Length: 375
Ligand SMILES: *[C@@H]1O[C@H](CO)[C@@H](O[C@@H]2O[C@H](CO)[C@@H](O[C@@H]3O[C@H](CO)[C@@H](O)[C@H](O)[C@@H]3O)[C@H](O)[C@H]2NC(C)=O)[C@H](O)[C@H]1NC(C)=O
Ligand SMILES: *[C@@H]1O[C@H](CO)[C@@H](O)[C@H](O)[C@H]1NC(C)=O
Ligand SMILES: *[C@@H]1O[C@H](CO)[C@@H](O)[C@H](O)[C@H]1NC(C)=O
Ligand SMILES: *[C@@H]1O[C@H](CO)[C@@H](O)[C@H](O)[C@H]1NC(C)=O
Picture: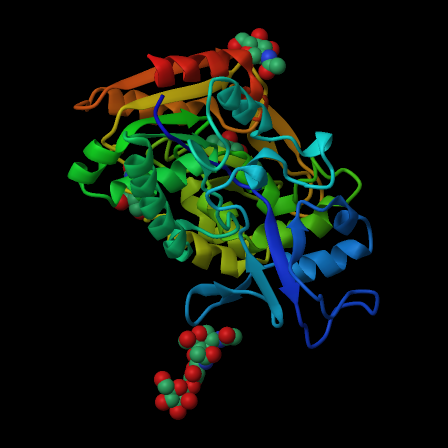
């Protein structure tokens, strides 16, 4: 069985922070921590009031002159568990059941004879940022893959979920063909948002608290806007129709060609700058150049377009299309398009009735993985 590298999506791996802040927004916020502590996921930090301290620490500060993000003053952040799997398996380490993500898949791999940190390793990253600001991650990824090839005597299978697929595609596009041919056995793509997703618009406009219902959407919106990864996942014209209307308000429409207006109108000009920085990172048409298995969920209502009665401080009415609940079905066209441009094999696999996250622990998904690894 070949070695395996797991790549998480947005919000998909733990993050740690250390504090020595000059000042804070409220007296009850900690100025200093003695060591690094879990910033994501920690449910205790997401309660009302305390949320303001958390936002103050986890937000990214955009420098308009340098066109780059910085951490808040006195705040440092690291990605734990690179080369291990604990940070991908459970999001909140203290809070077992509720935070289960990659756990089920990893347990199955172990059942088939794999070993944590050895045959199977995770590649977590700072998912708040785009690939442009995770250069070190990609260096470590390349080196880890080479090490696993040497140790275990064979090329690696990449298994990526959601945004992890875009990160890994960027990575693969930048490696020479000879390297990919030697070191990569296959790339298993799970729920990949090729060409962005509709839900991005709602998040940016009015906030999205589906997971965190105890907190108001307009409060959490502040943090969500700050993450470059959010703006990076706005719909792209090669997958969606250039004329498709995503957002309707009482005064105006918004298509994918109206992002500048959108950002100005919602009062977040930084987001336009973020989008300009990142929209050109991944070459739309260039395939990864390796054996690809594209798994996508269907039959789950997925937000397609939005009507705002009041813009942008009031929650919108939502029209639904097909997909996995998060990633729109229309994303799977890119895999379809790559199939016709094939040196390497491209296999498409529908997962009817499988939700975006549930697919990672689904028996059918695991059975397909078995096929790839042992066949
Ligand atoms: C955003 O990032 C930019 C670029 O890194 C920062 O630019 C700052 O600009 C000042 C001058 O306006 C820099 O000071 C000058 O440095 C040059 C050497 O290149 C020297 O010849 C001058 O005498 C002067 O000292 C400053 O170094 C630089 N600030 C930095 C690097 O922190 C800008 O400050 C950043 N903005 C924020 C809010 O972080
Ligand atoms: C999509 O956007 C890019 C960048 O603006 C542009 O080069 C390309 O022509 C666009 N596709 C269209 C207009 O169909
Ligand atoms: C958006 O465009 C469509 C098609 O041109 C039009 O029917 C509609 O009136 C527009 N919506 C708004 C809110 O202006
Ligand atoms: C797994 O997928 C099957 C069919 O693909 C679906 O019927 C089922 O609801 C899913 N179950 C879980 C636990 O994800």
